[PDB]
Image (cartoon, rainbow, N blue to C red; front, side):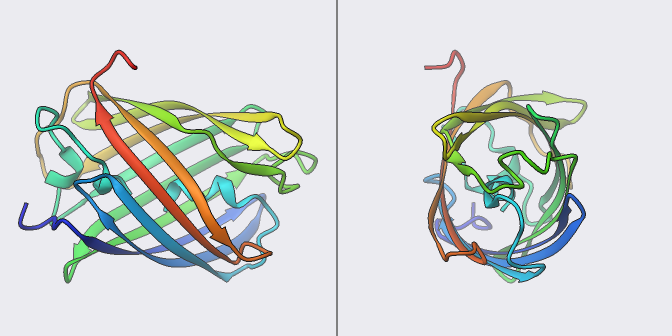
Length: 218
C-alpha cells in the first residue's frame, strides 16, 4: 500500500501477429489503482497501419487498476513489487482465435507491461480483418481461484458498423510471482472505451473503468 500509490504510471510493449501480419506497439498510461480508472496512449511502431480491427488488441493493454472493496482480497495489487503474469484465450464466434501472454512488474515506481499476442484463423471476410468493429460493450468478468491462481471468464461482445454484434469468450489465468492471498469468487464490471484515434489507428487512446463487486450479479 506504500508500493501501489494512489496515482501510478505504466509503460507497455506488445509484440504480435494477426493472420500472420507482424507488428509492435509501444505505449504509456496512467491512472488511479484504488479508484479503478486508467488511460493509455498507444503507438504502432512496426507493422503499421494494422490491417485488422484495433478492438482485438485493446483489452490487452492492466488489472492492478481494479477498484476492490475491503472484503475482497486484491491479489494482483498484493503481488507487487514482483508482479504477476497472465495468459488469455479469446475465441470468437466465427472461428478467430487470439492467445496472449503478459508479464507485469514494477520498476522505478512505474508498472512495466510486456505483451505477446497471436491472432489466427480470422476469416478474410469477417469484421476483424475488414475493420468493421466499433468497440466492446460493457462486460463482467467472473473471477474464481483455482490451482493456486486467479482465473476469470467472460462473454464479450463487439458492436459492428452494420448495427449487429460479434461475440467472443475470454478465459484468463492470472498468477502472482509470489504466493499472496487469493480472493473467493466475485465479479469485475468493466467498461473499456477508445477515446480517440487517428485515421489509420496508428495512434490510439483508451480509457478503462473496472470495479469488483460480490456475485449475484446486479
